[PDB]
Image 1: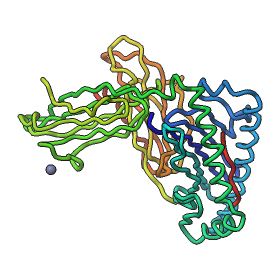
Image 2: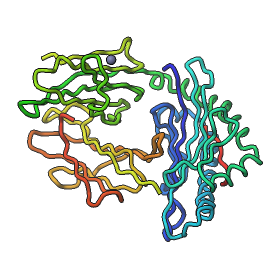
Image 3: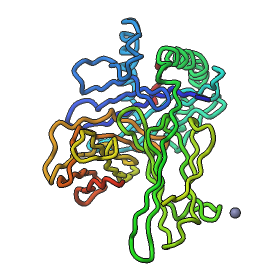
Image 4: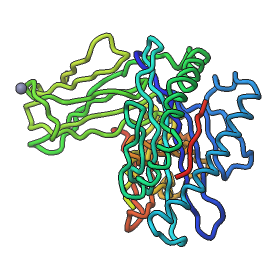
Length: 277
Length: 100
Length: 8
Ligand SMILES: [Zn+2]
């Protein structure tokens, strides 16, 4: 595809009175998950979730296991620090989420990097786009920001994101080339569903596509139907492809005023669909 | 702490045709916090061998999960997904509609 | 290949 991403997603959830926090880590290349770690699982190892990652030698699995376990410990500590910063009790359950990653172009060049945290579902701290300073969302987060400024955490993360992250992504793309580079276009069709004598639903379907990025829109007389479109979230089929549909309620007899529009990287050209009885 | 209610979609991997094996999906997304209960029902009863994807989250930090199982649809059998989350007064049941 | 994180 024209650009690619490598992303890791970390979730810690405290369990007061039931031991250490639940810690789940998942790694993705674009929309394809390739590793996982789960503190509840018996192996206590980073585990493969895509076939091409099993091409990695044993050094890899040992090293990635060491890092994700160290990460779990740090975010465990992080949950505690946050309780103190926010003056919250030890009785409540809380969530700490962390994401990082890099985007690179099809030319192999770095586009952007991310390194950011959320606490109980709200932005806590994030590396800004220029990778040189931090967006801290509230008073607590300024303490962390001052701490990370003094230790030059931004420079360490910039070096990681522009270096190892990109190197890793390129290597994964090579090893998983046969699947990771595909841009399968959506198979599209439209269905018609009468609601009454006055109205019917037109539903535009996109099926079998990868990557998940897609634009599915309705127009009426060449005009955006943004505030009258029912648009579901892009959803996994389970077999490595994605699905989406968009629908509009149209007055009987007015079907031909409507067109469905489909943009997807796999398409030679954007699609315009009409109801063809 | 922010709280967001799950979006719930129930759907087959492939277009259903009665008698042909397929996969029944329940995709729950946009929710927070992450603890959630999800059952696939066949005629009101919990299906047993149901698997799900590893917990992950979107740009806005809300979580998403895919629950799935093999199945062979018929003309008669009703399927549904039942979801409980702290944002819900009572469990939410969404019936499988083969046209959705 | 993952990076690292720091304490709050
Ligand atoms: Zn116009």
